[PDB]
Length: 107
Ligand SMILES: [Ca+2]
Ligand SMILES: [Ca+2]
Ligand SMILES: [Mg+2]
Image (cartoon, rainbow, N blue to C red; front, side):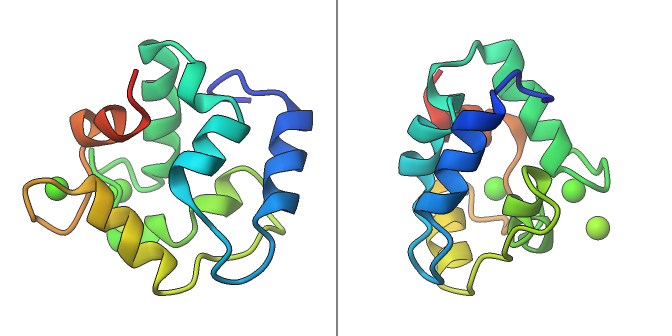
């Protein structure tokens, strides 16, 4: 829901990355809808993965990225989390802020 994605695109996507170390951010962002959502929604998501409301997705909310879409879903492996944060975290503080998230989805 949060980001107004549909179940189908969400069930699709997860199937597509259910192997360990087959997760890829922009590919799942294309997939599940999010890379063509408005920037309002690209925020609504952000704040959902920010499970603890800190303003930031820390490395440990990032590895539970999937589960925000489906509870039973798998954790990301440590490499999968290391590339994302690698791609997201331009100021090197170890966690992703909104403006960084938005930035990595595009739009
Ligand atoms: Ca957080
Ligand atoms: Ca950062
Ligand atoms: Mg926390």
